Length: 116
Length: 116
Length: 116
Length: 116
Ligand SMILES: [Re]
Ligand SMILES: [Re]
Ligand SMILES: [Re]
Ligand SMILES: [Re]
Image 1 (cartoon, each protein chain N blue to C red):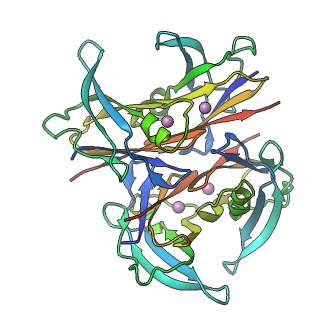
Image 2 (tube, rainbow over the protein chains, first blue to last red):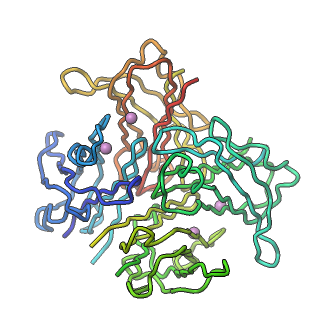
């Protein structure tokens, strides 16, 4: 419940299905440790990355790999990786939605952060 | 010139060229009155809409004829047109740049106000 | 189920609660007829505007009035109305989400259009 | 100059001034190599990053130090920095303009490619 990633295609007005998502957390030594991963559903969303027990304060990186999405559309992408880096839970637990909007020459990302 | 409009196409990664733009100003009876109109240049820009003297404080609406633009490129888009409203306060001379970024199912608009 | 409007605040990373939403449909005579209305919930979303029986093909306008949201934040907005106009159901029934992202000097809107 | 970066602040409706920008180029071993860096001017622009000869085909990452920018304005933002990737193909001379629009919880990036 506390972390959900959503990916949308601005050209098609559609969810982006089968986008690979990787989450890393910055460790003590300043390296990126693996945290969680998954693939977006039919609705362009990925739920169940983590639990409130595991999603502690820290610096997180969310990566998306869109190759499979673009190729399913018959598109040969010129690049296919996007990353965002943020601080989480630093004023207490919140629920986070990280949304990306894709097009060929533009990219947006927005975070919505709510209470219970 | 105190008012410029700039339009960008996120599908082509290009200025949006020859796009029709209409600017309206809210009248005292709450109707939108025509103010100026034009078509974007080869750089995606439209200047010469107003002199400094004609550009008074008020609530302005910029309407961008995205429908015709996308259809001319063989694309059937979502919106009939793109619209943004912006307010000009009274001030010393200020330049207002209205920037739109277009995709077939999404757009974003920003008003940049600078003291020249 | 077929039409949902969502409004988000990009400054705060939050849903925009109590935003008034009005939907109009273009009639035979080219006037805008009232269609539906409501207010966004805690989650920034408004569901239950219409039913598949009523949401027929046509040209629709979705208006938002953000005054109550901004004033609750202690903000005195310089304008507080946004509109989008689109064609619906023209290739068969779809579900539509119309999302707006607000900030003081920018505005985005995106439509996501899916099947069952 | 064939590469320019432009950064806009959606909270203030202004160019984002004195913002640090780093540009990296992907190397043959898949690492990001430093390419150039600078700070935005009073118009929100950064030019002089590269000569035409140094700007070869490749995959480029533009990192914008949004964290420091927002903190300097008294705002605690979501992202540690903003990142966009763009690819340059081999071609006749082309100008690449990378445009970012910043809010504390959202940003959008676009690559505009023009034939001068
Ligand atoms: Re991508
Ligand atoms: Re404004
Ligand atoms: Re608004
Ligand atoms: Re690109």
